[PDB]
Each structure stands twice: as C-alpha cells, then as structure tokens.
Image (cartoon, helix red, strand yellow):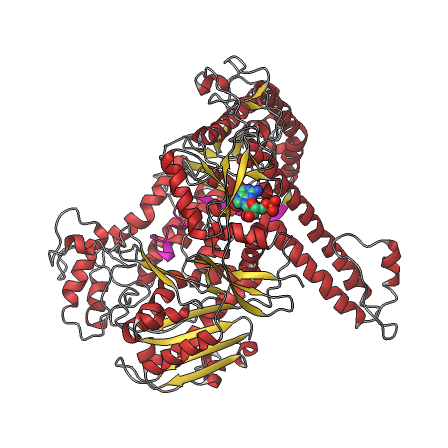
Amino acid sequence: MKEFYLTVEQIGDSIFERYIDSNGRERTREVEYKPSLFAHCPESQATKYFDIYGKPCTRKLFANMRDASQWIKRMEDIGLEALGMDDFKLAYLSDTYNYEIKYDHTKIRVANFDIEVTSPDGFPEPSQAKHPIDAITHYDSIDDRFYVFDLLNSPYGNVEEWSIEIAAKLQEQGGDEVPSEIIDKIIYMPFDNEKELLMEYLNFWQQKTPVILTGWNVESFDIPYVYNRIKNIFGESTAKRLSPHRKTRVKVIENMYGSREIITLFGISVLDYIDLYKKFSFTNQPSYSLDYISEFELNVGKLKYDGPISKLRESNHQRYISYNIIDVYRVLQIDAKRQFINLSLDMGYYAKIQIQSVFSPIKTWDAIIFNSLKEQNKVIPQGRSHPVQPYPGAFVKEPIPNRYKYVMSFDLTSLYPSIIRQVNISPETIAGTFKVAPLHDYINAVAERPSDVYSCSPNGMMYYKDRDGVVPTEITKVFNQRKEHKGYMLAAQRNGEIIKEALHNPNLSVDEPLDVDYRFDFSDEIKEKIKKLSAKSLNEMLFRAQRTEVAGMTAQINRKLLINSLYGALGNVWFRYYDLRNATAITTFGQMALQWIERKVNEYLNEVCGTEGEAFVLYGDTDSIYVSADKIIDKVGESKFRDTNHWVDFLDKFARERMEPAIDRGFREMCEYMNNKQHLMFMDREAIAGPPLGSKGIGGFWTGKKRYALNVWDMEGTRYAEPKLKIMGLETQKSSTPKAVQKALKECIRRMLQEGEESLQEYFKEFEKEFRQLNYISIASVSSANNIAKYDVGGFPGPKCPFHIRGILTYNRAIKGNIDAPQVVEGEKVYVLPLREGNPFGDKCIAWPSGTEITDLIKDDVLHWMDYTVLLEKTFIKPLEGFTSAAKLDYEKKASLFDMFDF
Ligand SMILES: Nc1nc2c(ncn2[C@@H]2O[C@H](COP(=O)(O)O)[C@@H](O)[C@H]2O)c(=O)[nH]1
C-alpha cells in the first residue's frame, strides 16, 4: 500500500506531517521543504514553465522556506510579479503524493466528543472557563468505543455514580433507553475531583492523539472550553499538549458576539459537524438544534427530560450522563446514513488540501487547478487583493399576488458552471470588449448581435472560441468524472442484485470468491460461474460489490459539490483567478437567459392557445421557471378528465413533447446570437401542481418573491401517492412561530390547496376554540435575546426596545425573589407572551428561557394574565390574512342572507 498523509502544518522552515506509512502505521515526519517559485523570463529562454498567458517563466529554488516568503514580499515591493503556489503546504502535498490517492479510513482516527459543564445561568463562557467541566464523552473511531469521564464531586452538588443497567431500562422502567449494541462499547470512569478528570483525559489524548475531530458545535464551544479550562488551572504551557506538535493559536471573532475565540489545534483537523452538515445536507433547515436534526434525519430525537438543562446533573445525574452518550451517538448515527466525514476524506484526498480546507471553496479549487497545471509545466498567477464590488446577482421575477390552480416548473441544469463552459469564460480567454446596450434590449434580440467570431456575455465581453479556457476545460474534467463514477456506483448496484438473487439456491461445496472488477457489469461468462458458488464464497463476494457501490457514489457526490461551489470561488476576491468582469459576465448571462426564455415561452404558448399577450410565465428564480397551466386546461375542458392523476400524465406529455423541444430549439437561437462555443443550456420539467380535481382546492398561490405554496403531484417524473406540499418562505418554518401554530398554518394551507374555502373556514373555527385549552409553551413565541439585552438595562425598559427584550427585563425584574430555582436569562433564545391589560407585573409582556418551564412562584400568575386575543392575532391571524388576501379567499364566512333560517 502506497502511503498517504493525515495532517500537514508549517512551523518555521519545516513541514510537519502525520501520515500513514506503507503498512498502515501512523508516523510523524519533519521535512525542510525546499520550495520553488517562478518569475517571468525574457523570451530568449530555454524553458518549459509558461503561465496561463504563454509568457515564459524560470524556476527559482529556495533551499529555505522563509527565504521564499521574503523573496515574494520583495518582488511585490519592486512591482514585479512573483508566480507559483504561495501556499507551501499545498506545494508539498502535490510534490509528495504525485499520484491518484487511495485512502483507507478504518486507519484514520476520527475522535467525536461532547463536554458538559454546569452553570446557574444556562451558559458558561468558553472564553474564561470559570466553571468545572463535569462530563466528557469521547467516541474513538479506531477502538469503536465510548469513553466517559464522570465528575462525582462538584461545588454544584456531589453525586452518585452511574448505572449502565439503569441506562438500559425502558422509559417506563425509569430507564434511559441506551441501545444494546452500544452498551458493551461504553467505558465509564468516575472521578473525585476535576484535576484528576482533566489530567487523565489529557493523557488519553496524547496517547490517542486524534486526526479528525468532530462533535456538534464542537468548534465554537466544546474545544475552546476544554482548552481554556485546562489553561486556567494548569497553565498554557501544558494546554498546548493537545497539539501533537504542542503549537497553538488562538483567534477572536465578532458580530453581536465579540470575544468568540476559536482555537486552531496544530496537528489535527477540526471538522465541526454542524458546518459539515450545513454545507453538504442539500436541504435548507430552519434550526440546527441537534434534536431537530436527529429527529428529521433519524425520526428518534434527543433524550427527553424534566427540568432545565442547568439542573439535570444536580437533579438527575443518571440521565445527565446517559444523555451525553446519547448525543455523541446521534452524530455517529447521522454520519452513518449520510457519510459526511467520509465524503470530506474523499474530497480533500482528491484535491490534496488540508482536510478542513474543504470548508473553503477558494482553497479547494485553487489546489485542484494548481495540480492540473503543475503536471503540464504551467504556472499559476499570484494572489492579488481586489476591492469588493457590488455586481448583479440572480434574477427573481416579481410575481402577482394571486392564486394559480395548475402550475408546472422547469429547471436549468447547473447553470453557472454550464454558462462558464458555454461562453468559455476564463481569465486567459478574455478576447475584448464591445459597445454594450441595455440588457433589456438583448433579452429581446433587438440589440444588434455583437462579435461575429467571439463568444459573448450581455455585459459586453467576448472570449476566444479557439483556445480552451483553463477553467472550462477544468470543470469539464470533473463533470466527466461524475459521469464516470455515477456509472460505477450504478454497476455495482445492479451487480449487487445478481448476487442477492443467486443466494437463495446457494452452496455447491467449499469454494473461493473471485477476482472480478465490480465497477462494470458482469458478462454471461461470470454470470454463470456464479450459479456454481457457495453461500460462503458469495455473501463475502457481495460485501465487495456493496462496498464499491458505496465508494463509487461517495465519489460521484464529491463532484456534485465541486461544481456547485465553483461559481462561489470565482465570485470571491481572494481567488487567485478572480476578475470582476468574468464574474459579472456569468451572472448577467444567467440573468438574461432566463427572461429570454421567459419571452420565448410566453411567445410560443399564447400562440398555441390562440390568445394574445397572455403571460404564462408566472414566476422565475435563479435557474427555474413557473408556468401557469390554467389556460391550457380550460382549452381542453376540465370535464374531459375522469381522474386527477389522468390529467397529470397529459400535462406531462405536453411538456416533454411540445414544450421541451420548443424550449431547447428557442434556446439555440440565443447560443448563436451570443455566438457561444457549445449549446449547454438545458432545462427539463420538474414539478407539476394543482388541486385534486372535483376538489374546490386551488393548487397554489404566491405572496411575493420566494413566498409561495403548492400542491405537488409529480416531481422530476416520479409520481406521488398522496400530493406533497412544497412550502417556501411562508413562515410555517420560521422558528419564531409557536410550534402549535406552525402545524396549524400548515393545515390551513393544505386545506386551501386541496379542499378550498369551505374546508379552511371550519378549521379556523376549530383551532380558535381549542386554542385556549392548549399548553402555553406550544403557543408561546420564540426569538433570541441577541444579548442586546445590555443596550437597554435601565433596570427597566427605555425606547427602541424590541418587544422581545421588553419582556425579558420584566421577567428578571420580577425574578428578584429568586430562590436560585429561577434560571437566569443570559444573551440567548427565549419564549415571550402578551399579558393582558392591568397585569401586576408591569410592562405588557414576559419572556423566559427556551425549553424550560416557568418557576411556580409566578408561573400561574403569568398564565392568568395571558393576552389570548393579542396572541392569536399577531401569531396566527396576521400571517394567515397574508395568505387569504393573495388567494382572494375568506377564512371567516360572511353573512349569507340564508342565515337566520333553520335548515
Ligand atoms: N508547475 C508548477 N510547479 C510549481 C508551481 N509552484 C510551485 N511549483 C513546483 O515546481 C516543481 C515540480 O515540477 P515537475 O517536477 O513537475 O517538473 C515542484 O517543486 C512544484 O512544487 C506552479 O505554479 N506550477
């Protein structure tokens, strides 16, 4: 096995790298890199090494690493361009792993942890670590074990040990429900005092120094804390030991925040899972609380409990510890069905960057490219700083607030990267410039066609249609690769079927599984020798096909990500290959392509229906368009259908048959008009929506930009049993709306889209009546005290006070007769409730810690003085009104003269 690295780091004039050797052993190296740089030489040179612009370069070998840093500084000062990879780590890696990679993973020490601390006020400061760490869970990927560090004695109450068996019991058995398979994994360890707890943990670390490091919110909390705490009581001199190279760097951040430090641990690759998820989930979420995610992601949730989180140890150490183990597991479980860490491995291993650098598109891509060129003796530019310049972005049509029964949408595949490829946009393919007319004129083909030999953008640009641009040819490769791997992933799957089937008519003695590539399909030759196999040789044979199917796809996905992040790096100033023009070129082209096809579509359609100027294109956003089908349907009469579904196929066919070919054919025009290099602008149908047929429902309706809801039957061809609801921007998600109301509005909406006014009305009446009898929490509002709590503290209020913060002060004011039981409110997430007129608390609203009940000393008073109507209105009716207005509907039946009569 050809080795591979784990981590790299530059300290002084040397590279420090933990890597696995030939026979899988974690070793440490200190190499004094002799980095080489470049400078432009006069034409009359015997050289290879030419930049992306052709100009010749000569190599400059440095001997000593900081010499090169000096050198660079120098050239710049003079005015001379200094070329090459200014980042040496990356230089090293290419230079040392000059081959495709092949990494293991079972040989990579991913440590996953979560620490816990107790505090009167729910949150301690990672910055100063005043409070003792009381619990630490550390799952080790290599050992596949959970190490638990438990603090028996604390000034916040000493406690009893913990029971593995009680942890095992069911909910009703006063048990914690920790899953069996995990139970014999746990390695509990209790401790008297903190000094020992830490001490030991420290030793555990140096003994099993981690490579990747995860957790949930580990980076912003867990890590900074562990770090400081130890520093505080044992001195930084020793805290540094967390670095396998004992080098460390603190760094402060800001915002409303201010002193939010982050410690970079030299030697290890922190990869907070909250980010890891944020970036690759492909699913936009409203909150990132570990509960909510593990709930949607895995259905289960978080260990439920009584009382505030600052009490749980003091009030139920058994569960306190149990919950830690649960948490760490959650993540483990998520990474299993999502493979995020692995993916990270793959990605970084491809590009040859520090793993964490995965988070940065800039670093990632810069590397790739550098490598590509590197093997063709070309030289990369040099990072030039540029000013931030507010260029145009995606196009979003302003919709007409109304109801739209039948609707269907289409998607531009990949867009930005496709555009790049179509126009052949590159820093070194820039041909010229041209007199540019108002964009509007271009999307109408009114403006006169620019260059007769250049690929252009509507902003005035023109690029050569000859030389293949560094960037487009680069993307292309990746885009080819995904096609390649998606291919494999699919082969080992349908090949996986072949094995699963021949296992029912198993065994024909004692044999050997075979040397077969699993990436491609089988061949009758091997399809036969297979029937002849045993349940021992097969099965094992299956594992191999099952594992290559996982690999192939984990690689395929990798590509998908690259492609998406690319525009984001071009649009970024630190990008070595940045250029505002290229940037504005892309975005404006997109901007046009859309409204151009918008025109084309309306054009085509109202001609096919024999109508005039009717605009079907209802809305558009970035890469998608939403057409109105209302007309088409009425044309062939609603009654001519005998089945909700029956229509869907019709629209579907119409799309793929009439529409799509028209679209592409009308898109070709544009390609010639701008006279680009290839066609690449493809759009395919995707959603199809409308009310159930017979149902007096409305299908969909829009409130405004990015604010709409639709009843969907078909999506990208795959049909639905029950209609699904694509809700967008309409606050059924906004974490601020009461959990009760969120389900309530969702229903109203469904009742609108599928049933119609009549249905909606009766519901409104129901939840309205029952509203009063519900649990307060579910109907309370939620916001976060952005700690601007300071900004006011006149002990009392003081103008410009947001309603939010208004209630907080009135809480703390009345909290005065504390008893310690009232959990102090500290700069983070709250509840808030109305409060009728003349209430004895003063002010006219209260708020308290999220996820906590309210201290009985006042709780009942509060409830008594709740302003239900005010509540109802601001939280439920107002957002509701918004919807009804747009859809021309009424949620309250007005006077029918037939009232007063008894039918
Ligand atoms: N081709 C190329 N090599 C670079 C660049 N910056 C640094 N290098 C160094 O050039 C040397 C290798 O060239 P090769 O061995 O492939 O002919 C290595 O020391 C490599 O790290 C760059 O922009 N292009």
Q: What residue lies at 14% left-to-right and 61% top-to-bottom? A: 841
Residue 130: x, y in percent? 25, 71
Residue 463: x, y in percent? 55, 24
Question: Is 711 on the left or on the right of 554, as rendered?
Answer: left
The magenta stretch spans residue 740 = yes
Question: Is 679 on the left or on the right of 889, as rendered?
Answer: right
User: Where 434 sits versus 186, above or below?
Assistant: above
Ligand 1 lies in quarter: top right
**Closer to the camera in the image, 155 or 595:** 155
Q: Residue 177: in sight, yes or no?
A: no
**Closer to the camera in the image, 307 or 863:** 307
User: Where 20 sits versus 182, above or below?
Assistant: above
Q: Splitting the image into 4 quarters, where does residue 541 fall?
A: bottom right
Residues drawn in magenta: 719-741
Residue 402: x, y in percent? 43, 33
**Closer to the camera in the image, 331 or 86:** 86
Name the image quarter holding the C terminus: top left
Q: What residue lies at 49% left-to-right and 70% top-to-bottom? A: 329
Name the image quarter holding the N terminus: bottom right
Residue 305: x, y in percent? 38, 73
Q: What residue lies at 77% left-to-right and 63% top-to-bottom? A: 500
The magenta stretch spans residue 599 = no
Q: What residue lies at 32% left-to-right and 73% top-to-bottom? A: 230
Q: Splitting the image into 4 quarters, where does residue 321 fall?
A: bottom left
**Closer to the camera in the image, 593 or 235:** 235
